[PDB]
Image: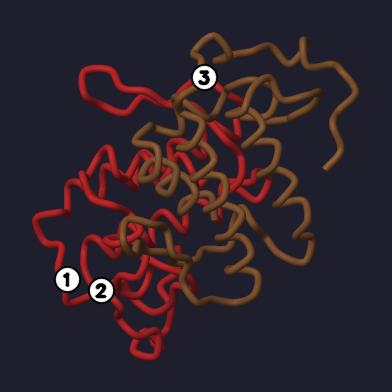
Chain colours: A brown, B red
């Protein structure tokens, strides 16, 4: 669920997701459209695609468990849905971490009006 | 949404919600029933009741903004639904903080089978 996802982002990046990953670029936030502005934004695009590929699940609300082994996120053994949702979230958190090096505050609060370009397909 | 709720619990209590408030007593977790075991558990019961009183909203998934003024949680100015959801979450986070003093690890992983008592009404 989004509860676990927020904690996972914080644990993996060191950044509060509400201030760094909630209104960024064209995809990190509500109503994603157009093309990703940078690598960080593309993490959000790919996460949206991952959730969209799970119509038989409830990715935002279905709780799951995770932990760490050797510093790394390990998803718990849950239902098929919980496992798939957790893997979407894990992939995204690791993507944010790997792309911290090109994070740019200039894309915070980027206006949706400038994302009115043909939306990239998953 | 649950994303904000998790961050709010962490910020207010200092505790990871996934390890302290996700499998506790009869109500802090999935499928709450019976009677709250202690004050902390009753925070979860009341939060469930608060969300249940918002059938015209989507409390688990509707994102909102919050911040702090003088150390205290202040909900952002959103839709009526966002405002109401945020106030449910704020109340719960502050309830957890106020009842840290009676938190008991013995109620972690409390079995649902022992909560098969007539469920308290909201």
Q: Is residue B48 above or below residue B81?
A: below
Chain identifier of the residue bearing label 1 in the image: B
Q: CA distance from mark 3 to mark 1?
A: 37 Å
- Name the residue beneath numbered marker 1: B105
Which residue: 42% across, 64% down? A66
For this rendering, which residue is in front, A40 or A109? A40
- Name the residue beneath numbered marker 3: B77
Q: Residues within 10 Å of mark 3 (few under 14, many from 20)?
A: few
Which residue: 25% across, 74% down? B108
- Name the residue beneath numbered marker 2: B108
Decide which of tag 3 and tag 1 comes sooner along the chain: 3
Which residue: 37% across, 23% down? B67
Q: Position of residue A49 (x, y in %)?
A: 75, 46
Chain identifier of the residue bearing label 2 in the image: B
Q: CA distance from mark 2 to mark 3?
A: 36 Å
Q: Secondary structure at mark 3?
A: loop
For this rendering, which residue is in front, B29 or A121? A121
Decide which of tag 2 and tag 3 comes sooner along the chain: 3
């Amino acid at each position: 669920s989004l509860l676990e996802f927020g904690m996972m982002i914080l644990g993996e990046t060191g950044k509060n997701p509400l201030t760094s990953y909630s209104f960024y670029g064209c995809y990190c936030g509500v109503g994603g459209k157009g093309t990703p502005k940078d690598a960080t934004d593309r993490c959000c695009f790919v996460h949206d695609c991952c959730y969209g590929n799970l119509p038989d699940c409830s990715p935002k609300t279905d709780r799951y468990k995770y932990h760490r082994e050797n510093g790394a996120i390990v998803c718990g053994k849950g239902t098929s849905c919980e496992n798939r949702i957790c893997e979407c979230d894990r992939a995204a958190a690791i993507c944010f971490r790997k792309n911290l090096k090109t994070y740019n505050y200039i894309y915070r609060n980027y206006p949706d009006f400038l994302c009115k370009k043909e939306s990239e397909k998953c």
